[PDB]
Amino acid sequence: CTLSAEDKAAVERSKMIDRNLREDGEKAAREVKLLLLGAGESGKSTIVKQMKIITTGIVETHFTFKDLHFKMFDVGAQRSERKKWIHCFEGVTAIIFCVALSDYDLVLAEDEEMNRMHESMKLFDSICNNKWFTDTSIILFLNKKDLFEEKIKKSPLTICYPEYAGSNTYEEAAAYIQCQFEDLNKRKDTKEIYTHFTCSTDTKNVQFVFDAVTDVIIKNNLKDCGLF
Amino acid sequence: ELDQLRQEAEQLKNQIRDARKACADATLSQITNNIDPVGRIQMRTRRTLRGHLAKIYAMHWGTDSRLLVSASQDGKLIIWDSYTTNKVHAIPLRSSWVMTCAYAPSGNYVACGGLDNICSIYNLKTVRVSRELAGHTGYLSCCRFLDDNQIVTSSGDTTCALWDIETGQQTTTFTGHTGDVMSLSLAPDTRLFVSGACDASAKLWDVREGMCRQTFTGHESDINAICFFPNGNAFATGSDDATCRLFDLRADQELMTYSHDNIICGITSVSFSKSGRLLLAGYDDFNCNVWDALKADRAGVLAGHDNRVSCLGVTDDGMAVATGSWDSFLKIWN
Amino acid sequence: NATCKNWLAAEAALEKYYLSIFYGIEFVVGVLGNTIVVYGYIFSLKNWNSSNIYLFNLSVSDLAFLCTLPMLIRSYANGNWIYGDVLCISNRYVLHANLYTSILFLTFISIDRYLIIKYPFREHLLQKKEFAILISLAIWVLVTLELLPILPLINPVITDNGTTCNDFASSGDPNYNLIYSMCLTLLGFLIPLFVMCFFYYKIALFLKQRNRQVATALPLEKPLNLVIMAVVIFSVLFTPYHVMRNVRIASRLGSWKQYQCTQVVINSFYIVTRPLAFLNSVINPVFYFLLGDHFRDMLMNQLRHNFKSLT
Amino acid sequence: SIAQARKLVEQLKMEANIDRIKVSKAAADLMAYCEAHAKEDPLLTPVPASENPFRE
């Protein structure tokens, strides 16, 4: 009898394994994967603590909001080289980029010349225009909404932007920063940026993340269906 | 003093360069110009392995020459039987970001690692996580077994380490490199090993003493792969500048450069044959090039992958060649 | 003029030239479109899903329907059927079967498009790639079973030593043909039309409701326009043919008017209307496959690849 | 970085007494090894299908 006795058993084992594998795949395709990025001291820890439910290098945070499972990946200790492991995150649903609004008037404290806002701009420009991230959406969080308001009445925004021309208030100045950050995008036809002004006392950030992720998923499905 | 040390190492570098040049009386191409070319190498896919649901990042054969191990970035480590398609094992990982894979020479253990900076050792003849080594401060790039109780790893913190699985401690640390170490290879006698880093450099380390022996340069970019010649007296390196290079140990210099036009992609892996005549290298164009190691002539081409070639291996008996790819398919060529 | 003698000549002119040339252009355009669409769906598509199965089945049905025109085109240009009786019988049967299978596949494409909007991760029984094959096989078998009763009607007329194989509406007994046509138009056209309209109305309502959650992003306007256009094209291209076929069959019942000139009017308008319903088999490839940016880009990328191998 | 420079200079000093050989000798040795095992390389010289584990 061809393919009998132990061989048959072996085949059976393989089949069983295959079944389990398929199951796992069906379980792993229902999770929204987000990549958390920040310039540094940008108030991302508060973001993690906000939507917190349920080693070194990678840090994983699982939570659920309205029958939707989110897995957030944080790379803070990975300081070796971005070019050598960034492509691992090619299939993420979205990139949550955190920027602090209170570091415009304060220097990097190192090199005596780097400005934290300019460093954040450089990081955002590098991440947004990347060969691995061409259709991945970015959710931009602007933290420190209170320190910015408290400091804008004393330190003019021209310290960071020599070409700024306008009033000096909380409004008409955060819009300038948001526009400056959004103008770094060069693929507006295929990519979207969702900007939210996050406050340290605001619990509505999870709602914004959920809305942006649902929009991204719906648009991806429509593109697949040919509408798209 | 700054002057008593600085500006003085350059003198030693100049002396080393002069010594290397003084012994380059001829070239390998001149010696091999009177050798019959191999001809045309034609290999056709014989087995296709399916089951991975994401990119395949590493693979290893094992001295059995029949069983194979593969790792993919979906949290699974699959052990196949090559002669058929049957899966022998499927180990679920605690971390989905894997970059390396190893098969113990005895076939009793397996190793894994990745972005979590931890090397996990699983026992097969018990399936069950046997050990977890965590000393590094960067992503694991490679890991190769020496015995059932010894392992050598390299991390992205510009460091390599020889461990002791019995106690879980770090037996020895190899320092002196500058960039992220991306690959390493063990000599057939397991007394020395070569490591290539992102600083366009390769180094020869002696396991028993933990001291650098020789340093090889010449590449114009990061080095992604490395392989020892079957006789143990030379090795080959592939870098991001779309070129491969052969270095020798006794002469302590470069011998030949395998490069060609219409090739502008980096090399992801390299490997030799049972006799060393051929040199197989996988590229980012989802293909593999087979070069004549003694003539620097492209003897053959292997095509059939869709996204990329990330892992490449040759069995201990030279029967077939296994290639993995970013489309989650492993192919056997004969 | 409005004389009956000019209408009588006008049907000869329409059945000789209009049908032949229109079918000739339709055959070429649809065959080329369906060949391009089919190419790259098997040699360039991996990981098929429920939507792809339905789309591929629709394309295959359109290609099979189009492969039938050439014999009818020549026979209309020549004016006589020179082939065997079995050839024309099989030609007519395959034509009608493929038309109605295409209608059913369009209905199921609309159903799948609604399901994808309702279940974004495909966690549904009808969204896995096992129900799709069963549904396609059932559609094929049921359409063949439904078209089986056509054989007793479409039989060649043996007269003057020349076998004349006339169209479906003109052949057979008026009563049986009328009842069968009225049953076929109800089962194969109206029910699918209503189901497609209902599901596309649901999809449009969802898209409009979901446009209020758009805070600052590109609105969902293009998909709504395409959803409306699908139903508009289907209804406009299919309604006149089914409306006029039954009128032509009834005009042969005799007592309806017992008039001959009326008959010529009715027949001229049916003949003009026949190819409008067939234009769908050529319109579909562009509207469902090439209009999608993803499919067109993939097809172009895989066409430039392998071009160096054969050029 | 006096200690770093001292360590680097010491490493360079130790990496200077390898007692190198000529390139011709290494090339000849590599050629001899390659030619000695020519018939034991299935990839270089394919074996008949009667003894090919991966047949068909």
Image (tube, helix red, strand yellow):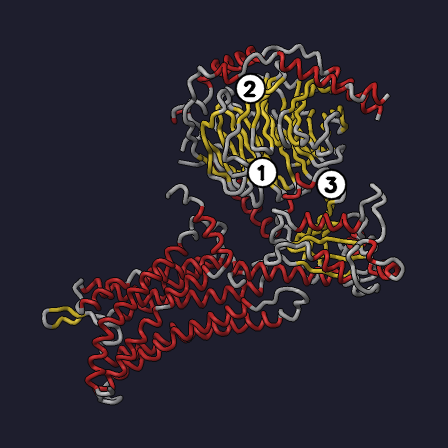
Task: Pick whichever of labels 1 and 2 is earlier in the sequence.
Answer: 1
Left or right of A49: which side holds C138?
left
From the image, tell me which residue sits under label 3.
Answer: A78
Q: Residues within 10 Å of mark 1 (few under 14, many from 20)?
A: many
From the image, tell me which residue sits under label 1.
Answer: B78
Left or right of A24: which side holds C28?
left
Type of the residue with mark 3? Gln
| Near-viewer residue (B80 or B229) | B229
Q: Say if residue B125 shows up in the picture.
A: no
Type of the residue with mark 1? Ile
- Give the letter of the chain under mark 2: B
Q: Position of residue C60 (x, y in %)?
A: 37, 58
Label 2: element kind:
loop
Label 1: element kind:
strand
Q: CA distance from mark 3 to mark 1?
A: 27 Å
- Say whether mark 1 and mark 3 are on the same chain: no
Q: Residues within 10 Å of mark 3 (few under 14, many from 20)?
A: many
Residue sticking out furthest to the right = A154
* CB-based contact (under 8 Å), mark 3 and mark 1: no
Q: Position of residue B116 (x, y in %)?
A: 71, 39
- Say whether mark 2 and mark 3 are on the same chain: no
- Give the letter of the chain under mark 1: B
Q: Any mark on residue B230, and which?
A: 2
Q: Quadrant of residue B69?
A: top right
* CB-based contact (under 8 Å), mark 3 and mark 2: no
